[PDB]
Length: 434
Ligand SMILES: [Mg+2]
Image (cartoon, rainbow, N blue to C red; front, top):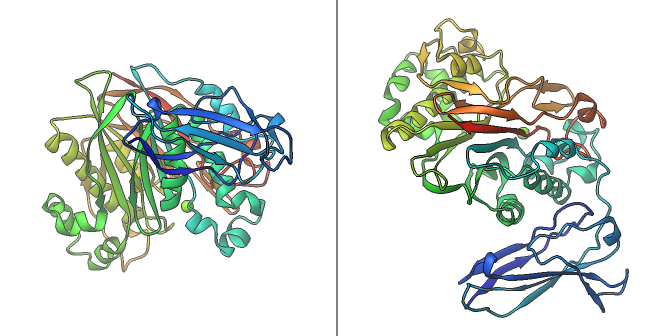
């Protein structure tokens, strides 16, 4: 019979922030299920009396009038033929006041609705993993300017849920996703808004890609670890051969845990349209320029194999936190299709790990959101590290959702803040099929 295997509410509920219940449904569908939201009839009624709201949807966004009230969700699982046993769940917390403003509030004016069939609204966002943000070092050395409550996972997830669902996007590529964030925050929020997701963890965090089901279906997945592909896959034998005279650089590349997530999607709107969506988080060290070049060379060879060998020539979207600014060898290589043997990034970490080589690729990739002043803004550092790279053979930029202003970014010195849930800024752009 239709039954909710998991039924959970968030612990932190804020006025103006969507309440996205976790509902794992067996033998049924949410479109076939019944939802009704209630609010406490009066503050402090200890849940003795409940007032029906007019909200019959899975998601409820409390108003300022609900501050001080608990909420209750009634849900009846259904499969389109019959209902299962009804369930009810009350919030343990009362609705609280949320932040006055968020950096994404103005950005949401550019993403008012789900886009037409000819477009692909694409997001790339490093959402700052709680595995790193939870530490004393993050709170006192990295982000001392941030209100400690605003670093806490439950607070940041509320903002990230509002931010991402507010973009009404089609393809969402995320980095620094914790295992529990994927299953308890992103999957319930994004599935309520019509997106399905896949997760590729490294150790305690990793990559996620979400896609809008009304526009896409997932065909296949081709995720890799760069070290595994480079050392063991004969596809990368020529690059491994270039690294034979540089054993110190080769050992440092092969130590890295960096992964590449690859998902091939099929348009539910045009039968002839498939797209290869790649997502990554490259090695982070400031002196790791040569490592990022080699990781990018593996990534592009892997994506070429998936998109042109496994599939008979499909276009590509490559999102990620590339930990590379536009002045680097890695960025030049992506945009120009080659990098010379004498590039200074081949000795980015000194002579011992020097690995001068010539690399070439035949993709025609454009940074969809261009080269912002920065996509990462913290105390002591800022830089453009994130990109949405698009295949110019098949895609064009319809619009770029502007990044928050510098005044918005610096209201609480830097990021994250009470108004911005990550140390990175989400990239959002509308792409058009050519
Ligand atoms: Mg980070």
